[PDB]
Every structure is written in C-alpha cells, then in structure tokens.
Length: 312
Ligand SMILES: *CCC(=O)Nc1cc(Nc2ncc(C(=O)OC(C)C)c(-c3cn(C)c4ccccc34)n2)c(OC)cc1N(C)CCN(C)C
Image (cartoon, rainbow, N blue to C red):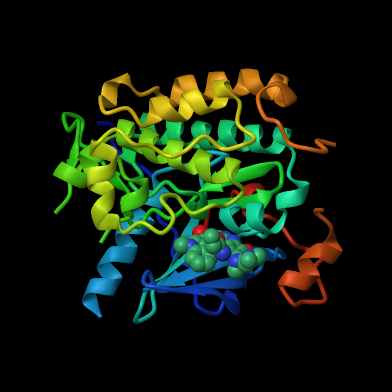
C-alpha cells in the first residue's frame, strides 16, 4: 500500500538494564527491565525479549511488525538492541496478561471490566485490520494489562503484514484451539480468522481463565469443529453475549462479524453491563507502585512508554 515511513530506533545496551525473567518458553525469554535514555532524565519500565542467524531474523521480523503499528490498544515497540542476539524492547505492562489476571482476581472482576476489555481488544484488532495486519495469535495470554482499565494486544511473532492485493496469508507450530477452521485445514489466515480467535479470547475472559476444549487433544479438534460442535455457553453470559461468540465461530468467514461491528455491540453492552453479564456481587499508578516491581528506590523520574514520544 503506502510507504512504511516508521522509524526503527536502536538502543544502547548501557541505556537499559534487565531486572527479572517474566517467562522462558519456546519463544525465548522475556525480561522485566528499566530503560534510561542517556541525558533524558527519564526512567521507562520496559520488557525485553531475546530468542544464531535464525533467531536474529525472527525477532527483527517482530520488530518490523511492531514498529508499523501505533494504537492505544496495541503494545508499542520502543526499539532494538544490536547485541549478538538482538533484543526486542517494548513497553512493560505491569499487571501481566489478561489470562492470569482473570484467574487471580476471579472473585473481584465485575461485568463492566469484562465488557470494557472486549471493546478495547476489538479496537486494537480493528486498527490492525486497518493496517492490513493479521495477528494469527490472538488469545487471552497475548492481551496484556497496562491498568485494570487499559489492555493492549501483544506478541507479534506470528503477525504477518498483507500485500495490497493479498487477501489471505498462506502459512507452511501453531495454537490449534484459537485458530479458525479454515486455518487448521488449509493454513489460510485472514482478518476474519482473527475474529474466530477473538471469539475464543472473549470465551476465556467470560470463563475467568478456563482452558478451551479442556482435556481434548489438538488433533481431534479439527474433527470437532467440523462436526458443528463449539465452545459451551459460559454461566455468566447472557444469550446476547454468547450469540456474538457463536457468530465469530461460524464456518463462513465472511458471515462472522467484523471488528468494527464488535466494537459497537460490546460498547452498547458496556452502557448497561449487568443486563448482559450476570455475576454475583457486581459491586494504582503511584511512585511507590513502580518501586516494587522494578526493585528500585528512586522512581521520581518514571515515565510510561505511552507518555514518552521522543525522537532519538
Ligand atoms: C500471559 C503471561 C504473561 O503475560 N506474563 C507476565 C507479563 C507481564 N507483562 C509483560 N509486558 C510486556 C511483555 C512484552 O510485550 O514482551 C515483549 C515481547 C518484550 C510481556 C510478555 C510478552 N510475552 C510474549 C511474554 C511471555 C512471557 C512473559 C511475559 C511476556 N509481558 C508481567 O509484568 C510484570 C508479568 C507477567 N507474569 C510473570 C506475571 C505472573 N502472574 C501470574 C501474576
């Protein structure tokens, strides 16, 4: 489409420090860290990722994808550090992923927060659809929590930018339980295939972190969805909400709702949240807070990445 004039920033290894490991899985290792631009008098909480020539190619692909997106509900890239293994510096989300958050605070999450998260996730995905970007890994684990009122979409290791005349992406290890049926059978990925993963993501939030298709091997899932079986209706979900999930899981990809329409539907429900989610008993940004998770004492000059918009 248009020329991608995004600026790729290079960060010095001495400007930032690692603090603790947040996760060490197949992707690599994600660190909690602090970035201090030299001479800026600013401390920025960051997340650092590192995955050989093949490792440097994949993370530079992720840096290329993240540098092309800038949206309040999409994690922003801060830059890369050119070590032997090039590292990915992103904005740190202090409260973690939404999957662990709904499990830890299951008895304290109201209907207003669940519906608000659905609106924000759809806003981020609709922006990615505007950017011709297919995420291919939309899940509750990849929706991180900046604040309980603000979430962002993350993990672009599988994200693929589309050509202007490219309607679908043809793939050649994936999360089977979140993929659309056409993605499992024909390796076809589309913005409508992300709507399917969006439906599973909402199902994770409404079940407060239940594993979809729990106890079922991923090999048998292709035959389950093909027979017409879907995820069950969560107990707190009214039919208004569960109908939206079923629409995201329809066989016809074009029949599924668009992220633009999902923003509207969940926004209407957010006006009257107790009418669409039935939860019993439906009724923190400080300098001290950052001192704990960053394990630092002097946090007067802390600035979140959303408030740091600095050309180098
Ligand atoms: C769902 C598990 C999880 O997210 N764990 C987690 C995450 C975070 N916050 C955070 N912030 C930024 C990033 C990130 O974008 O990393 C870039 C790619 C460098 C991440 C993150 C992204 N991926 C792919 C991860 C994998 C494993 C771990 C983190 C990431 N995450 C925090 O903030 C403190 C904590 C946290 N866990 C450890 C919290 C444990 N809960 C049980 C409370």
